[PDB]
Length: 341
DNA sequence: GGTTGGATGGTAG
DNA sequence: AACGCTACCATCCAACC
Ligand SMILES: Nc1ccn([C@H]2C[C@H](O)[C@@H](COP(=O)(O)OP(=O)(O)OP(=O)(O)O)O2)c(=O)n1
Ligand SMILES: [Ca+2]
Ligand SMILES: [Ca+2]
Ligand SMILES: [Ca+2]
Ligand SMILES: [Ca+2]
View 1 (tube, protein in one colour):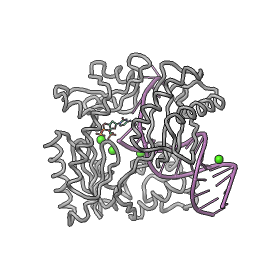
View 2: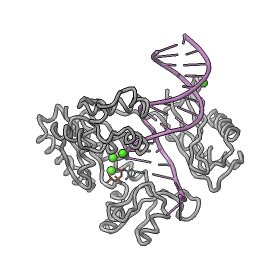
View 3: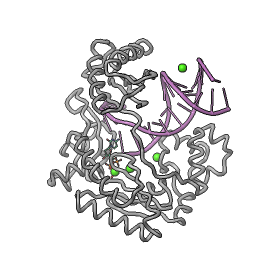
């Protein structure tokens, strides 16, 4: 098979640049303001000009302003980026019937029946890039390989505004030479566990006892890495179905006062219920982020669907459980609905 | 021993 | 050191077939 993966370039910042062209060439930082103080929050993303100086996703806005105090700091307008994304995804639908929308700015296309080889795949990749630039003036990176994982890795290698094929021979070289930390799904915790076992490359997972690898990183990740290393990973492109919808907000101050927290939680429920749009959940979880940014959650699954009124009542009980069973103050509070009918 | 549900862990967008 | 918000799959544990 052949898989073509598309990853939009510095997406949120690039959309802002398209809607206001004077931003291009100079550092733009898209921010998630919590409302705590002036400028409390995190960077969602920045364009490559700000990113050159270390302003990247996840860092505090305060750290970013220390590095580049003269950059443009824009509030995140997620709804705008979602609508642009949906338009681009609709363009991609024209090139394959088999498409997997992986996120707000990623999609996998199974183009096995559309092209005969990697040269034709590459030309299709170029066609897709030109189409998205024509219609939306958004640059993207395309990665192409035998499966979803190596397609994603290919795009990682080609980013800013690139295109890359990893053919069968390069898959073999990467199994030997790619830092296993750069494999999709291997974060810092798993990477460091692997390094302690002396595993630096995918091929190293074949030289360890399965029971030992499973003991350290778990069965799923062990099976996943071994399948990749054996050149056998072949997970199909399929339609992802949304499994949960939720909202969590930062409170104006930390609190353990039930009556102070309730209005935030209730607003999170109202917004979550609107986003449900005909979906009726059977499960509710109240999620608290404590003072030190730990996550505590209490939930319940009902035999039937949950009305909004039941969500209110139950959410209070679950919040009460969090307060009873955890003595830390709550910083952020929210809700998540799942198990849709 | 497998499935379910609840609490938590790890991950990536 | 600071510090947002969305949502996926996985693991551990105990209840229950
Ligand atoms: N911690 C993060 C990471 C990403 N995003 C959002 C903003 C990004 O623009 C978008 C896509 O994530 P990417 O990791 O692909 O980031 P970029 O597209 O901005 O950069 P890149 O050029 O590496 O693809 O998701 C976010 O809100 N919070
Ligand atoms: Ca990506
Ligand atoms: Ca991207
Ligand atoms: Ca990694
Ligand atoms: Ca139980």
